Amino acid sequence: XXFXXYX
Ligand SMILES: *[C@@H]1O[C@H](CO)[C@@H](O)[C@H](O)[C@H]1O[C@@H]1O[C@@H](C)[C@H](O)[C@@H](O)[C@H]1O
Ligand SMILES: *[C@H]1O[C@H](CO)[C@@H](O)[C@H](O)[C@@H]1O
Ligand SMILES: *[C@H]1C[C@H](N)[C@@H](OC)[C@H](C)O1
Ligand SMILES: [Cl-]
């Protein structure tokens, strides 16, 4: 990953 969220 490396980004975040939450979707
Ligand atoms: C997500 O990132 C925030 C900001 O740094 C941090 O406070 C949370 O603990 C962190 O969540 C962790 O990492 C994610 C990728 C997992 O889905 C979540 O369950 C928790 O382990
Ligand atoms: C979850 O999915 C969305 C839609 O593709 C992305 O924008 C996001 O960075 C993550 O991959
Ligand atoms: C992260 C927080 C967000 N409110 C949620 O959407 C329902 C997602 C599943 O997790
Ligand atoms: Cl998510």
Image (tube, helix red, strand yellow):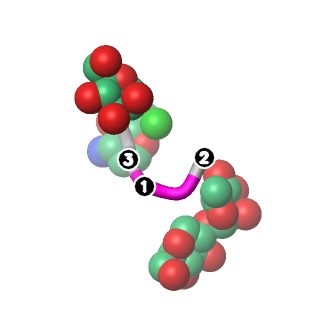
Q: Secondary structure at mark 2?
A: loop
Q: Is mark 1 within 8 Å of ligand 2?
A: yes
Q: Which residues lie in the magenta part?
A: 2-4
Measure the C-alpha gap from mark 2 to mark 3: 10 Å
Q: Is mark 2 within 8 Å of ligand 1?
A: yes
Q: Secondary structure at mark 3?
A: loop
Q: Image quarter for residue 6?
A: top left
Q: Secondary structure at mark 1?
A: loop
Instruction: For marks 2 and 3, give the one nearer the viewer.
Output: 2
Residue at label 3? 5
Q: Is mark 3 within 8 Å of ligand 4?
A: yes
Above or below, 1 against 4 in this view is above
Q: Image quarter for residue 2?
A: bottom right
Residue at label 1? 3
Image quarter where the C terminus lies is top left
Measure the C-alpha gap from mark 1 to mark 3: 7 Å
Residue at label 2? 1
In the image, is 3 to the left or to the right of 2?
left
Residue at horizontal 60%, vertical 46%? 1
